[PDB]
Amino acid sequence: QHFSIPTCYFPSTAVFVDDSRDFLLNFVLQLDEGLAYRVFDSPFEALDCIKQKRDLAAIHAEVYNSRRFSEISVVVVDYAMPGMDGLEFCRRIEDTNIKKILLTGQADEKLAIAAFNEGLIHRYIKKSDPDVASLITQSIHDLQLQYFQSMSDMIVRMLSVTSPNCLHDKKYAELFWRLCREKGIVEFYLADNSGSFLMLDDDANISFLIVKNEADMQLHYDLALDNGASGDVLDQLHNGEKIPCFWVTPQWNEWSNCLVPANRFVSDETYFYAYVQGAVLFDVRLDKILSYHQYLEELDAEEMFLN
C-alpha cells in the first residue's frame, strides 16, 4: 500500500534451496541474465549461510558498499527438502525480512495456504506446475521489490525522517519505474526530502531524477523574488516551466543555468521533475563505487552453481 517507490533499491541475491539438480538446471538456465543467486542442496547449510550473512544523506551512501548486491532478499525453498521441510526452514528465518517462495507438492497445498495466510511465506507454487520456472522468476522480481518496500519502513524510522508523499503515489510510481527501465537504471537511492533520486545503471553511470512538489516551487519562487532574480526566472518558477537543479541559495545572476526544463505530473498531488545526467545534486565518488556489471564479473567460479 505504501512505498510504491522504495527509499532505495539495488539488485539483490536470491537463494535457491532444492535437492533436485535436474530441477535447478532447468530453472536457473531459463532465468534472465543479471540475477545473482546462490544454490544450496541442504537446508542446514542454507540456514548457516543466511545467519552468517546477517539523516537522509545516509541512504545514498549505501552505493559505496561493494557488498550491497550480496544482500539476500528472496529465498526459494522446496517443501520436500530432506532433513528439514520447507515450512520449518521458513520459520527459522521468519525473524528477518527475507521473502519466502515455497515449492509445494501434490499434497502440500493446505499446509502452504495456512502458512501464506499467517505471513510465514509470501508465495507458494506447485513444483510440478508446467509454468513453474516462469512463475518463480516473476515472484522473485515481485518479492525483491517487496523486500526494499519493507526496508523503507525501518529506514525512515532509523533516520527519523518523513517519507516524501510521491513514494506512495501509485500513478507516479508507475511513471517512476517505467522511466527507470527507459534509462537502464538498476539501482536508485533517495536524495532529498522532496523525492529526488540518485540513479545508476549497471556500469555505475551517475544520474539524478530531481523532483519538486508545489510547496517547493513556491519556496524557490519566493527565494528568487526575495533575491531579485531575472524577469524570466520569476516567470519560469511561477509557471513551473523549470525547476532548480542545485542542492544554499544561488546568486541573483546565477539563476539562469541553475534551472532545467521540467515535466508536470498530476496524481495524488502535482509533481515537477526532470531526469538529468551526471552528478548534479551532489558529489559522487565514482572511484569508490563497484558497478553491478563488475560485481557479476567478479563472482568467484568456485562458489557458482554453473561451473
Image (cartoon, grey):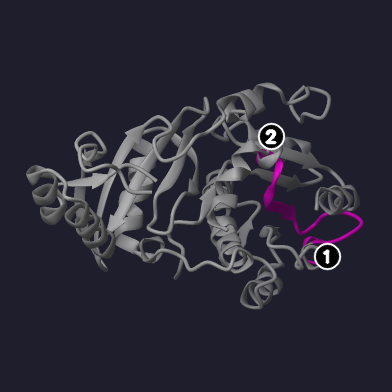
Residue 292, numbered label: none
Residue occupying the point 81% across, 61% down: 89
Tell me the magenta residue range: 69-89
Rendered view: 178 above or below 143? above
Residue occupying the point 74% across, 39% down: 38
* Number of residues whose C-alpha sits closer than 10 Å to that of mark 1, classed few (under 14), some (14–19) or many (20 or more): few
Image position, residue 289 (x, y; %): 61, 30
Is residue 61 shown to the viewer in this render? yes
Give the alpha-carbon distance from disc 1 to disc 2, as whole Å. 28 Å
Q: Can you tell which of label 1 and label 2 is closer to the viewer? A: 2
Q: Are marks 1 and 2 in contact (CB under 8 Å)?
A: no
Image position, residue 284 (x, y; %): 52, 33
Is 289 in front, or is 246? 246
* Number of residues whose C-alpha sits closer than 10 Å to that of mark 2, classed few (under 14), some (14–19) or many (20 or more): some
Name the residue type under label 2: Ser
At mark 2, the secondary structure is: loop
Residue occupying the point 58% across, 41% down: 11
Q: Is residue 140 left or right of residue 87?
A: left
Q: Quadrant of the N terminus?
A: bottom left
Residue behind mark 1? 92
Of the image marks 1 and 2, the number of the one nearer the N terminus: 2
Q: Picture quarter containing residue 183?
A: top left
Magenta span includes 16: no
Q: Quadrant of the C terminus?
A: top right
Name the residue type under label 1: Arg
Image position, residue 266 (x, y; %): 20, 61
Q: Picture quarter containing residue 122?
A: bottom right
Image position, residue 152 (x, y; %): 55, 62
Is 81 in front, or is 67? 67
Residue behind mark 2? 66
